[PDB]
Amino acid sequence: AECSVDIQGNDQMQFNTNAITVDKSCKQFTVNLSHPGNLPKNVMGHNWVLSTAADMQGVVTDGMASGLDKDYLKPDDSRVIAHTKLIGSGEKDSVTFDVSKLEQYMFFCAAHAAMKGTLTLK
Ligand SMILES: [Cu+]
């Protein structure tokens, strides 16, 4: 089994996939986020955030209200299963989470909530 994925967010405000699979045998899963291109984090920074699909809009609403100071996520939001730091070009971050926390899930960038995709156990 594959229990990690590499994902990119670029200067064009897009991730390089819209779908992540978590093998049903994994007990931990690691997301390795990178940022090809050239724009720094104060221009085009990205993160990677995981919630249920049903919770995504509420996470984004409360994150918007929390603002830039908090990477557009409400601190300690119970609906956020895992998230990375905000990265700019040439930077990287990885997050690992317990698969026991996984229903339909989605990932998104809190800076650019249009950047999104699905995560599913398979
Ligand atoms: Cu972003």
Image: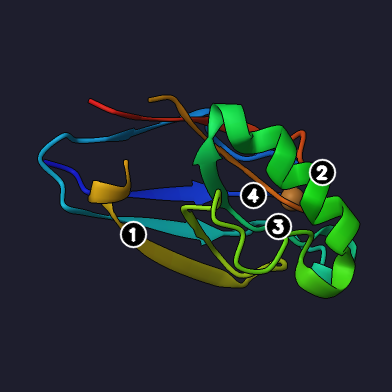
Q: Position of residue 4 (x, y in %)?
A: 29, 51
Q: Quadrant of the C terminus?
A: top left
Q: Is residue 90 left or right of residue 93?
A: right
Is disc 4 in contact with disc 2, using a CB cutoff of under 8 Å?
Answer: no
At 73% from the left edge and 34% from the top edge, which residue is drawn? 57
- For badge 3, the amino acid type reads His
Is disc 3 in contact with disc 4, using a CB cutoff of under 8 Å?
Answer: yes
Q: CA distance from mark 4 to mark 2?
A: 22 Å
Q: Which residue is mark 4?
A: 9
Q: CA distance from mark 1 to mark 2?
A: 24 Å
Q: Is residue 58 left or right of residue 95?
A: right
- For badge 2, the amino acid type reads Thr
Q: Is mark 2 within 8 Å of ligand 1?
A: no
Q: Is mark 4 within 8 Å of ligand 1?
A: yes
At 32% from the left edge and 48% from the top edge, which residue is drawn? 101
Nearer the observer, disc 1 or disc 2? 2
The answer to which quarter of the image holds residue 53 is: top right
Residue 61's label in the rendered image is 2
Q: Is mark 3 within 8 Å of ligand 1?
A: yes
Nearer the observer, disc 4 or disc 1? 1
Q: Earlier in the sequence, mark 2 or mark 3?
A: 3
Q: Which residue is mark 3?
A: 46
Residue 97's label in the rendered image is 1
Q: Is residue 74 above or below residue 120?
A: below
Q: Position of residue 105 (x, y in %)?
A: 46, 32
The answer to which quarter of the image holds residue 39 is: bottom right
